[PDB]
Every structure is written in structure tokens, then in C-alpha cells.
Amino acid sequence: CTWEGNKLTC
Image 1 (cartoon, rainbow, N blue to C red):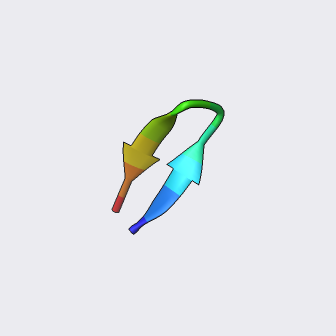
Image 2 (image 1 turned 30 degrees about the horizontal axis):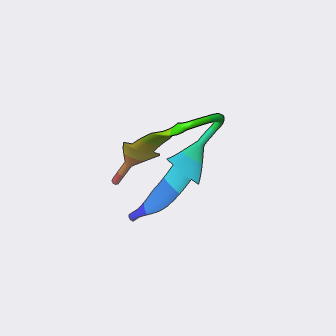
Image 3 (image 1 turned 180 degrees about the horizontal axis):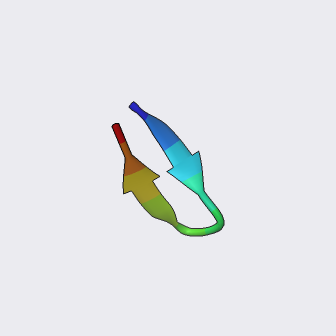
């Protein structure tokens, strides 16, 4: 799980 702009994406 990592960050995308300011959302969490897994």
C-alpha cells in the first residue's frame, strides 16, 4: 500500500 497524490492505493 502506497500514496497517490493524497489518496492511499494498494
